[PDB]
Image 1 (cartoon, rainbow, N blue to C red):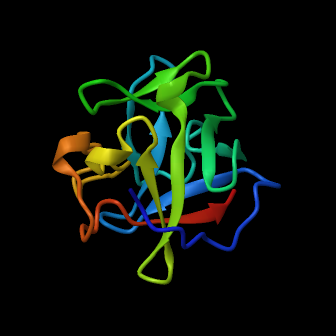
Image 2 (image 1 turned 180 degrees about the horizontal axis):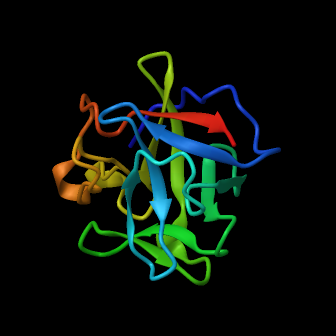
Length: 140
Protein backbone atom coordinates (compact mmCIF):
# COMPACT_ATOMS: atom_id res chain seq x y z
CA UNK A 1 0.00 0.00 0.00
CA UNK A 2 2.93 2.33 0.67
CA UNK A 3 6.37 3.30 -0.45
CA UNK A 4 9.50 2.08 1.27
CA UNK A 5 11.72 5.10 1.78
CA UNK A 6 13.01 4.60 5.34
CA UNK A 7 14.40 7.26 7.67
CA UNK A 8 18.10 7.10 8.62
CA UNK A 9 17.87 6.60 12.36
CA UNK A 10 18.26 3.81 14.82
CA UNK A 11 16.37 2.72 17.83
CA UNK A 12 19.35 2.81 20.20
CA UNK A 13 18.08 5.60 22.36
CA UNK A 14 14.72 7.06 23.27
CA UNK A 15 13.48 10.03 21.40
CA UNK A 16 11.09 12.85 21.42
CA UNK A 17 8.65 12.84 18.48
CA UNK A 18 8.51 16.53 17.51
CA UNK A 19 5.61 17.42 15.28
CA UNK A 20 6.43 20.20 12.95
CA UNK A 21 2.80 21.19 12.54
CA UNK A 22 2.46 23.11 15.84
CA UNK A 23 5.75 22.20 17.40
CA UNK A 24 4.34 19.68 19.84
CA UNK A 25 5.93 16.58 21.25
CA UNK A 26 3.80 13.43 21.10
CA UNK A 27 2.67 12.53 24.59
CA UNK A 28 1.27 9.30 26.09
CA UNK A 29 -0.38 10.22 29.39
CA UNK A 30 -0.69 7.70 32.21
CA UNK A 31 -4.43 7.39 31.69
CA UNK A 32 -3.95 6.24 28.11
CA UNK A 33 -4.64 9.65 26.70
CA UNK A 34 -2.54 10.72 23.68
CA UNK A 35 -1.94 14.32 22.67
CA UNK A 36 0.86 16.81 22.09
CA UNK A 37 2.63 19.23 24.42
CA UNK A 38 5.08 22.07 23.90
CA UNK A 39 6.60 21.37 27.34
CA UNK A 40 9.98 19.85 26.79
CA UNK A 41 10.05 19.13 30.46
CA UNK A 42 7.07 16.79 30.33
CA UNK A 43 7.78 13.33 31.70
CA UNK A 44 5.53 11.61 29.28
CA UNK A 45 7.09 12.61 25.99
CA UNK A 46 10.05 10.22 26.10
CA UNK A 47 9.43 7.35 23.74
CA UNK A 48 11.42 4.26 22.94
CA UNK A 49 10.99 3.07 19.40
CA UNK A 50 11.72 -0.45 18.38
CA UNK A 51 11.66 -2.40 15.20
CA UNK A 52 9.45 -5.37 14.69
CA UNK A 53 10.11 -6.05 11.06
CA UNK A 54 12.16 -3.68 8.89
CA UNK A 55 10.18 -0.45 8.72
CA UNK A 56 7.63 -1.61 11.37
CA UNK A 57 7.85 -0.14 14.83
CA UNK A 58 6.49 -0.02 18.28
CA UNK A 59 6.40 3.32 20.01
CA UNK A 60 6.55 3.08 23.77
CA UNK A 61 6.45 5.48 26.62
CA UNK A 62 9.54 5.12 28.74
CA UNK A 63 7.82 6.58 31.67
CA UNK A 64 4.80 4.31 31.75
CA UNK A 65 5.59 1.38 29.52
CA UNK A 66 2.48 2.14 27.44
CA UNK A 67 2.47 1.49 23.70
CA UNK A 68 1.16 3.99 21.21
CA UNK A 69 -1.81 2.48 19.41
CA UNK A 70 -4.63 3.50 17.02
CA UNK A 71 -8.13 2.04 17.58
CA UNK A 72 -10.80 0.83 15.22
CA UNK A 73 -12.15 4.36 15.01
CA UNK A 74 -8.82 6.04 14.31
CA UNK A 75 -8.19 7.31 17.89
CA UNK A 76 -4.70 7.13 19.33
CA UNK A 77 -4.50 5.50 22.71
CA UNK A 78 -2.02 4.13 25.24
CA UNK A 79 -2.00 0.35 25.35
CA UNK A 80 -0.74 -1.58 28.33
CA UNK A 81 0.23 -4.48 26.09
CA UNK A 82 1.46 -4.76 22.54
CA UNK A 83 -1.20 -5.71 20.03
CA UNK A 84 -1.92 -5.37 16.36
CA UNK A 85 -3.01 -1.81 16.84
CA UNK A 86 0.40 -0.90 18.15
CA UNK A 87 2.40 -1.38 14.97
CA UNK A 88 3.25 1.57 12.77
CA UNK A 89 4.99 1.76 9.43
CA UNK A 90 7.82 4.28 9.98
CA UNK A 91 8.72 6.07 6.75
CA UNK A 92 10.68 8.98 5.45
CA UNK A 93 8.61 11.84 4.13
CA UNK A 94 9.54 14.92 2.02
CA UNK A 95 13.09 13.52 2.07
CA UNK A 96 13.33 14.65 5.68
CA UNK A 97 10.62 13.74 8.19
CA UNK A 98 9.32 10.63 9.80
CA UNK A 99 5.67 9.59 9.33
CA UNK A 100 3.89 6.77 11.13
CA UNK A 101 1.17 4.84 9.44
CA UNK A 102 -1.12 2.51 11.28
CA UNK A 103 -0.15 -0.93 10.12
CA UNK A 104 -3.58 -2.32 10.89
CA UNK A 105 -5.22 0.50 8.89
CA UNK A 106 -2.49 0.94 6.28
CA UNK A 107 -4.89 0.48 3.33
CA UNK A 108 -6.75 3.54 4.61
CA UNK A 109 -3.69 5.76 5.05
CA UNK A 110 -4.30 6.52 8.72
CA UNK A 111 -1.39 8.39 10.24
CA UNK A 112 -0.19 9.49 13.61
CA UNK A 113 -0.60 13.26 13.61
CA UNK A 114 -0.85 16.32 15.79
CA UNK A 115 -2.92 19.43 15.12
CA UNK A 116 -1.64 22.94 15.61
CA UNK A 117 -3.73 23.00 18.77
CA UNK A 118 -1.98 20.07 20.36
CA UNK A 119 -4.77 17.59 19.87
CA UNK A 120 -4.07 14.43 17.93
CA UNK A 121 -5.71 13.80 14.65
CA UNK A 122 -8.17 10.94 14.09
CA UNK A 123 -7.03 8.40 11.43
CA UNK A 124 -9.62 9.16 8.76
CA UNK A 125 -8.79 12.90 9.06
CA UNK A 126 -5.17 12.36 8.20
CA UNK A 127 -3.60 12.13 4.82
CA UNK A 128 -0.52 12.30 2.74
CA UNK A 129 0.46 15.89 2.22
CA UNK A 130 -0.49 17.18 5.63
CA UNK A 131 1.82 19.04 8.07
CA UNK A 132 0.30 17.30 11.08
CA UNK A 133 1.80 13.96 10.16
CA UNK A 134 5.42 15.18 9.89
CA UNK A 135 7.73 14.30 12.73
CA UNK A 136 11.34 14.75 13.71
CA UNK A 137 12.76 12.44 16.26
CA UNK A 138 14.81 14.45 18.76
CA UNK A 139 17.13 13.08 21.34
CA UNK A 140 15.93 13.32 24.88
